[PDB]
Image 1 (cartoon, helix red, strand yellow):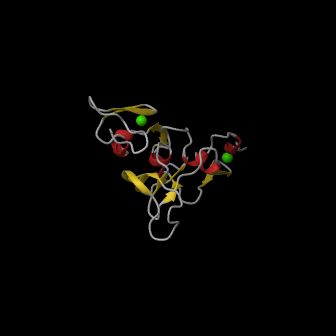
Image 2: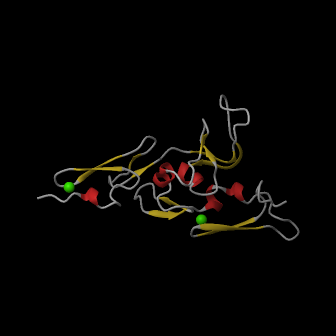
Image 3: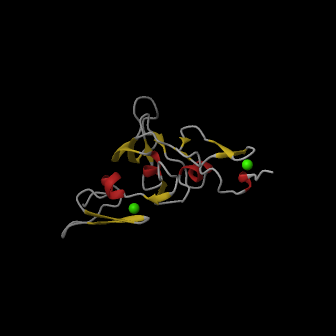
Length: 162
Ligand SMILES: [Ca+2]
Ligand SMILES: [Ca+2]
C-alpha cells in the first residue's frame, strides 16, 4: 500500500513531486538544487542585488545598476526590494508569475532557509545595506526600518538619506 505524497500541494517546496512506492521524488526547476533532506528546491548561487535595471543600453556586457547588496542569494534580493540580480545580471521575476511563486514561496519579506527550506526573515540590514545608505537600519520580521539622522531625509528612490 502506498500514500501519494504529491496529492498534498505543499509537497516538494519550490519543486515538482513524483510519487514513488514508499516515498517521493522532487524534480527541481533550473537554477535550483535539492536541499540536503530532499524536501525542497533552493537556489544556492550568489550575486549582487540591484535596485534599477531597464533596457538602458540593452544586454551585452553589463546591464543593471544602483547596487544594494553583494554576494547574496537571488531570493534574498528579489523576495525583498531587489529588482535585478547576479552577473550576467538577471532581472527579478514579476510578483504575479509562477517564477515568483517558486522563488518566494512565502511571498514578500521571507526566504526558504538554504538547508531546511523552512521560511525565515530576510534581514535587509545585513544583506541589502544599500537600502539605507547613511541611516540607522533596524530589521524586522517581514520588513525593516530605516531612520535618517536629524536633519536628513530618506530619498525613496536612491535610498540615500538625502
Ligand atoms: Ca509514496
Ligand atoms: Ca526583514
